[PDB]
Image 1 (cartoon, rainbow over the protein chains, first blue to last red):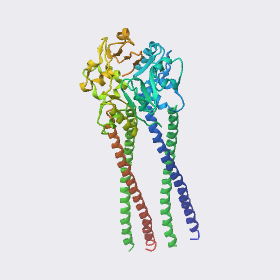
Image 2 (image 1 turned 30 degrees about the horizontal axis):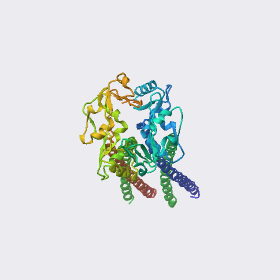
Image 3 (image 1 turned 45 degrees about the vertical axis):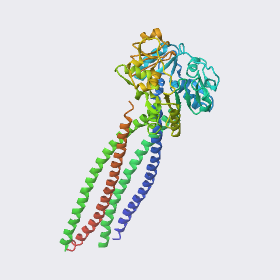
Length: 266
Length: 270
């Protein structure tokens, strides 16, 4: 008996350490699983954005030129969306409208440059795409002075002159639809809020949701996926060791009782 | 007596076995939920990522903004050209598809008044940008020289919107191959059956080559998002029971130890 005491002392001392090593874990677990919920939440968030902006560059044919600049041809200067820079903040929207689908056309030197640019497309299943042969592009010029010409508020290389005078040549920038009425139908004009009134009577309008900008997201998405995968791994091995502790505790607990009875006997 | 407490011990151990039996059942059942849940999660993501891309390509083209314009109540909207135009003879469609492109996502309306009320609605809800065709002010296009097969000859459409249709392909002619339009490149709007386009502005466009599955796809996702709730919920409830049973067996094991002890006090005595 006087020796049976130093037997139950160690045991409990070990079970105490267990309940100790247990809490020490639940803290981590509670901390990990928590930080994960946050990272996964910001992951699905930026996960959407990536797929979105990318899904667009397909329909818009943007990812096509990116993978088209990976080939050798003399004559290719890329799309207008890249070769034109608007001034400061003000007309961004306006000019984006005056171009819209035209800001995806790829400029080339001669018709032969385009004919072979297409082959790369049909020989790789990439999709349709528009090209502008500098030696054939018929530029457009402004006659009547109504609003500040959309061409006078941009900065483009002087070699791709005709290509821009074609996409924005007869395009003007006006303030409100009221300043346009006097000429709607005569001159091609777009308002600052995005309201294009084509000389053909066609009207374009609407406000989207705009929030390289893509490459950055890929970097951020990869980062999160890494953080995620790591956490899941850790957070999982802990939940394992946790039970490892719990099973031992249940097992340790049974042993103590089987002895507590023994002492009573003695 | 000693045999009385002994026959009472077997009564508990008999139950303890049952708990451990059902516990096994739970374990198995739970393992079956995880595997399936893990499978649903897969299809969900694999299929949900498509909506993020589909619903994104509906904004680019404007297909979404259009549909939203149907549940507006702004009488005057008639729809998309692509919806109002159809090709009578097949294998001649690829040409027209190319002859349209962006122009195909155009919405036909009565007048510029519907145009405004449509644009204002689009802005008020940031649905997107869209180009309208006011049949009231649209200016049709024609073809003087017959250097090929007119685009309008292989098309069917309600004579009531003839203007908008002649607006997109009014000056467009369908030819056979590249070397068939050369004599008139940048002179007339060419569109080879192969799938090419030679605008009068010298601009050349060509390449490779329904958006109606987004509705059926949004459903399949709404389904998986609903099926995951089921599986994910059923698991936490079963896992909860599994824990309850484990608490029970424990409760018995200590009791069984005490029962075991009394017989050793009844075996050392008797």
